[PDB]
Length: 381
Picture 1 (cartoon, rainbow, N blue to C red):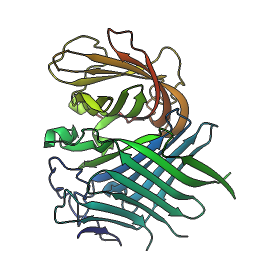
Picture 2 (spheres, rainbow, N blue to C red; picture 1 turned 180 degrees about the horizontal axis):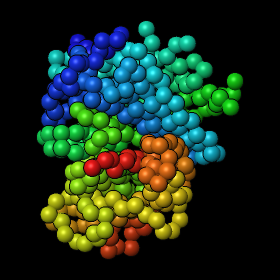
Picture 3 (cartoon, one colour; picture 1 turned 180 degrees about the vertical axis):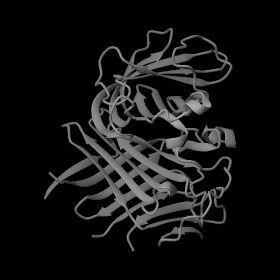
Picture 4 (cartoon, one colour; picture 1 turned 30 degrees about the vertical axis):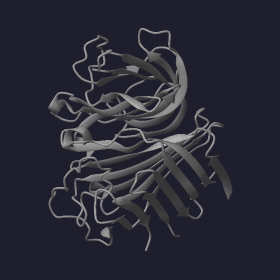
């Protein structure tokens, strides 16, 4: 059984060593820095869930971040309730181990455990099938309980290095694009008060599993990082969009997908200038545009946006375009990503209300989703 075990005080490499290669048609769930972690790399395993009506939302990211050494191993957790409660905490642990069962390192049952050797355990499990996941928390006085996914089998796996990229040589994609989700969690509201979050298997709760690794930290490559997961009528959409630093001229990159009743209708690996709204389509693409007009909570940091517009394009024969407005409905989290002031930037999570549909039609669907809206400084020239 393949094992990547990082612990103690010597897990970090001395130089930024390379990570192992993209495996085509695989979840790529085994760590790319298996034995020694590069000091500028970060690996991410993301699992999330939300109510189909936006009444609850949950996300956890399991991190191995070399640049945060010694505190490199983190389970970052955010939760939101319809009544206004929000809950955000990092579980920082000294041990992160990931195993993969089977002869094929790109196609085996995977288990991750972020843990102590107070007491903290946070773990995930993914079927070799990618058919199911289980996430379990055991952190007394903070969070306990589980999340599970049952995959709906949407097409999603990258067939090449290019399809796995979210930017050149940086990777973010979705080994499970869409899943029936359950949660059964208990949170300690430290304001000993407990709060429950329960989403059962027949309530239409949904979520996905996202996988990322970057040889270089985002703080030095991006000025903008947008995450989206949303569902509206037949449509399911998921986005990770990057806008680079000025030294690369605000390169616009994305790894995104739009589905209609489970069929992928835009394999969007091209991110368009936000002020275009034309009909050109030499490839599937998505346009992400900050919205400032109309309904929605106003974000607090660099950009005072009330939401985002997502316009998907298909290069298929019918040349369809879909447009959705994702408007800030509930402020989930909000954290500075720089010192305050005129150049100040932030990291904001929202539950969003979703409207829109097929352009040129009478379609007007309605739904719910989440966004993670990250801003980073423009840097020194």
